[PDB]
Each structure stands twice: as structure tokens, then as C-alpha cells.
Amino acid sequence: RKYSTFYEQRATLFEELPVTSKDIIFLGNSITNGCEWAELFQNKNVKNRGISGDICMGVYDRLDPIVKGKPAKIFLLIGINDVSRGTSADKIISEISMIVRKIKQESPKTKLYLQSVLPVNDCYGMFNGHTSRWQVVKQINDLLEPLAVKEGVAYIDLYSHFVEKETGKMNPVYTNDGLHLLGKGYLLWRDIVKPYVD
Amino acid sequence: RKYSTFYEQRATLFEELPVTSKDIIFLGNSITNGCEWAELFQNKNVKNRGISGDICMGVYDRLDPIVKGKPAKIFLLIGINDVSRGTSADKIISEISMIVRKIKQESPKTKLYLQSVLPVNDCYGMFNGHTSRWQVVKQINDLLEPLAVKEGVAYIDLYSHFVEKETGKMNPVYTNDGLHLLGKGYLLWRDIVKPYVD
């Protein structure tokens, strides 16, 4: 109920806001939703198309008001809420490939950047549906990078910078719940992807 | 737990993003948080300082990284989550006046715009703590406008445009849950406040 009403609130607002060929789109779930992307990059062309709670088919169904504008770049980060529903990495990758093919077909000039699913951590005892499945994150990214080269789009490895090598979980310094990012976490993200924005 | 962790996520990100003297700040709770304000006004200087779930003392405690930058304008809309906690309109107005005095003292050049609390509607059966108290919204705005003239700041009447005269509740066309706004609801909001932004 809460996800579906909030999804409709954001999606109908996105239909009222025009995308143009100069735009850089950050597309994803709550981890994308939570940032002021245009402020983070001091770039009037960076736009937030994140929706808290979103899943792969959720993004796919709302692509039209985005690809219609033929944006310059799209940065996609999606999948963790499908994990928390018990969906397998195989099925998640096939849904992500559906998203990739649609964007290429409807806006072939758009540069698409596939971002690694971020690690999670169960240390704070929250989002147990998500954090209890922290092993699935690597399974997804192991398939996601080959999908990127197979489809001729870019793969960006955020995972390696956020993960704790010794544990495979997200470094607690970047989060206060095991899933979402503190301000410092978005600063690190900015440092990794800034070259692809300019 | 969810509000407090999300509050910290947004507040720490706001501490990393500089405010400047040219900035227009939209400050409030989920109804402010939910919009892409810079896109809505096609104005690179409009910035989103909304936090879903926020309350009056919540805004007050995070004023420093905002007033420090001495922004040009601040649009404040806050109070409905205090209503849902059972707090009286008297106490809410005294907490809003605390917020007004702090901004005037720390950034006396900032123009402050106090926006009427929006009406709610119980017709969809959600946010019952909020929507069952729909009468308190008018009690707040009846005190809020005198507070604005007494303190020498502006009062903006959004309420009159969103309310259903015959019921006193929000017109269902603008919402799908009785509390938050659909895309059309933000378009109306844009039409009312656009003169104060340019």
C-alpha cells in the first residue's frame, strides 16, 4: 500500500517534468531517491528519477516519460528490493536486461551506465529481508558486468569501494541501517562516478 | 526507528551540500521531500530540504547548515506530523515561532515564507493519525497567518486552493492517500507560489 501509493505520487510527478537531450538521469530505488543529485554534482542537468521501494519491473513500467526525452545519460541502480522479495539473481538479471533493451531501442543515442548493486549489512538489525541475503549482491554483480559488455553498455563498480573485504558486507561507516547511505556515502559515490558525468 | 534513521541520512547529506546567498530553500516534511523543486521551477537555485516524517522540532534542530549560508528565500511547510502525534495547534504555533525567530536572528536578509498547512482527507482510509484530525489544520492556519504578520514574514495560502469548501478536507483529485500530493497537486502548488520565486 505505502510503496504503491508513493510510486504513483512520484511517477505522476515524473510525467509532468520534461526530460531533454541534455539531461543526466539517476534512475533507481530508495538509494537513488535519497540524494539531491543536481546539488551533489553542481550540474543543472542531473535529475532524480528514484522511487523508494522500487523494483525492476517498477522501473521498466515507468520508462516512457524518460526515454521519450532521449536523455544524454542514464545511471541505473536497481535490484535490492527484488532480492528482499526472494527473487533469484537469474531472474533479476533477466529483468535488468529487459530494461537495457528497451532504453537502447527507444533512445539509441542515450549512454546507459549499469551500476553494481551495493552491499548491505545486517549489523544494525534492520531491513532483515534485505540484509539477511547479503550474499546475493555479489551473485548479481557477477552476472551484471558480463551483461553490460554483452549489451555494449558501461558497468560501474561501486561495490568494491563500499564493501568490507573481510566480511562481504557494507562498511558500517557509510550507513546507519545497513542498506541506505549517510551523507559521506553519497560523497564517495560522487567521487567514483564524477568522471562519467563530465 | 525508520524516521530517525532516514532523518539522519538526509540531515547528514544536507550538511555536505553548501547553501549560498542565491538559494531558494523548500523546507519541510514528506510533502516538501516528495517534489523535484528545481525541475518544477526550472531554476537551478531552488533546493529541496524536505525530510519525510519531519516535525517542527526536527526542522528547528537542523537549521544550522541552512541559515549559515544566508539563503535568499525559505519556503516553510511543517506541522502535520505534529498533528498526527496529538500535539495541539497552540504548541505547534509556538514551535513554528521558534523556527521563525531563529532564522531572522541568524540570517536577517533571508525572506521567509510561511505556507499554510495543507488539508487532509480520510476518504482513502490511510494515515489515520493524520486524517482523523483534519479539523486541526484550519485551527493552525487561523493562528499561523497572524503569527506571520506579527513577525513580519509572508503567509502563503495554499489551503484555500486544495481544500473542498463543502467538506473542509483536501480535494481527492490532488491525492491518492489523503495526505500526499499527486503530480497535478504539485503543479497547482507551482502556480500559486511561482510569483514569489521570481
Image (cartoon, coloured by chain):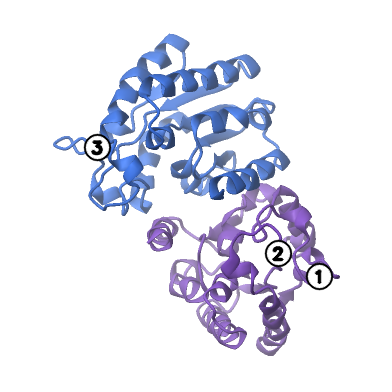
Chain colours: A blue, B purple
Residue A25: image location, x then y, percent: 56, 34
Q: Dot 3 lies on which element?
A: loop
> Separation of disc 3 and disc 1 at Cα?
53 Å
Asked if the residue under mark 1 is in contact with the one under mark 2, i.e. CB atoms within 8 Å, the reply is yes
| Number of marks in picture | 3
Query: What is the quadrant of residue B22 in the picture?
Result: bottom right
Q: Dot 1 lies on which element?
A: loop
Q: Which residue is mark 3?
A: A163
Q: Nearer the viewer, residue A154 or B122?
A: B122
Q: Which residue is mark 2?
A: B121
Q: Which residue is mark 1?
A: B167
Earlier-in-chain disc, 2 versus 1: 2
- The chain under label 3 reads A
Crowding at dot 3, Cα within 10 Å, few <14 / some 14-19 / many 20+, comes out as some
> Separation of disc 2 and disc 1 at Cα?
9 Å
- Picture residue at 51% right of the left edge, 71% below the top: B55
